[PDB]
Image (cartoon, grey):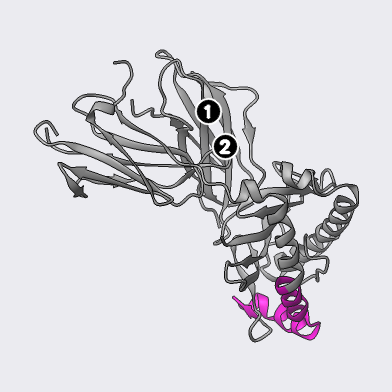
Amino acid sequence: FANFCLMMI
Amino acid sequence: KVSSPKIQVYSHYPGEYGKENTLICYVSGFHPPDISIELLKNGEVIADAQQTDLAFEKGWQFHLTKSVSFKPEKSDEYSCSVRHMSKTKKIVWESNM
Amino acid sequence: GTHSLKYVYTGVSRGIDFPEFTAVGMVDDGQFMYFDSNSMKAVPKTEWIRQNEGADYWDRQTQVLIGAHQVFKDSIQIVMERFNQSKGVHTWQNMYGCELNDDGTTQGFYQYAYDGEDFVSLDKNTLTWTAANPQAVITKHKWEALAVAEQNKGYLENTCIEWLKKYVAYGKDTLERKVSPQVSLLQKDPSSPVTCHATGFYPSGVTITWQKNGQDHDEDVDLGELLPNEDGSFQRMSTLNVGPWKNNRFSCVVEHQDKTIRKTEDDIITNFD
């Protein structure tokens, strides 16, 4: 399952 | 900026004439990802060929696989034509037989 | 055996060949998931995921990746500006994943790249981000303040592994399969070089060796690259170019999973003879 938390650079 | 595709054309099984087989074109190490791949029989695009979903390996270089069922016969020339940016390369399948 | 779960995201500025965002999920380097920003839907790519997960799983996966698309869109706009390259066609990539060993021990990685070159990389031992260039340093400071490394490490060491274990169970038969190579000796002409061709095997590890009379022989040998078949199996070949082969008995030995297959000159096939 993909990582649900992403942050823009 | 740009890294031209390595192109490798081969068949699943030995290219025995008259035997059901799969023609495969493995296109790797290219960038940018925008690209066109077609399998040709006697210079004409083979229909119903399938292409893997865009992916890449460690090192970031993209790779794609295009394949279609085929039945090689004495008369016919099979090839993989790849257009990437300003270059179009056509590679003829070698049966080694 | 060792197993892995990996995700690779591709972000693109300017079309048309591909959508703005593409995601592929893999177990042991075999695709089981797909998503892109055209369909806005995450979909199964193997039988074992189809039979073991359903609507709820995919709705959640879709929802996560729609967010990924949104973030990638904003991210690539930013990095392009930092390279003063905002006009042209460019790329933003992310790959991450975990490995589970027989050991029970685990490995994990988290990396990003712009235009096919390293941008930032996770060091989950020091909980820092390695910036490949000046353009990445601002991101490094931002992410280290937001504790992105801690979150990523948490995912890699826990969530990623827990799902990998599930997936391995789902597709145990396919993932643990051992398929022996089909081996043939090829020759265009009685005077031409001879190719030992192995195909249809899995896992991908294979050894092709030539023998003359023979204990093995590695002069005039050209070992080709490991190549993928269309069905998840692999193939590889080796070519022998030796002088008139006639007075000496050559053979090809292919070893896969501790088992060997031998082919001698009596086995050589050709078109059209």
Chain for numbered disc 1: B
- The extreme top residue here reads B75
The answer to whether C159 is drawn above or below residue C146 in the figure is above
According to the picture, the residue beneath numbered tag 1 turns out to be: B22
Q: Indicate the position of residue C165 as horizontal and vertical percent values.
A: 71, 62
Q: Are marks 1 and 2 on the same chain?
A: no
Chain for numbered disc 2: C
Disc number at residue C230? 2
Q: Quadrant of residue C187?
A: top left
- Say whether residue C61 is left or right of residue C257: right
Residues in magenta, as a range: C129-157
Give the residue at x 65% y 54%: C27
Between C265 and C129, the one lying in front of the other is C265
Q: Indicate the position of residue B23 as horizontal and vertical percent values.
A: 51, 29
Asked if marks 1 and 2 touch (Cβ < 8 Å), the reply is yes
Q: Looking at the image, can residue C49 be seen?
A: yes
Q: Indicate the position of residue C131 as horizontal and vertical percent values.
A: 63, 78
Amino acid type for the residue under numbered disc 2: Glu
Circle 1 SS class: strand
Amino acid type for the residue under numbered disc 1: Thr
The answer to whether C262 is drawn above or below residue C142 in the figure is above
Q: Indicate the position of residue C66 as horizontal and vertical percent values.
A: 85, 55
The reply to whether the magenta stretch includes residue C145 is yes
Circle 2 SS class: loop
The reply to whether the magenta stretch includes residue C91 is no
Give the residue at x 18% y 27%: C191
Q: Quadrant of residue C159?
A: bottom right
The answer to whether C81 is drawn above or below residue C246 in the figure is below
Give the residue at x 72% y 77%: C153
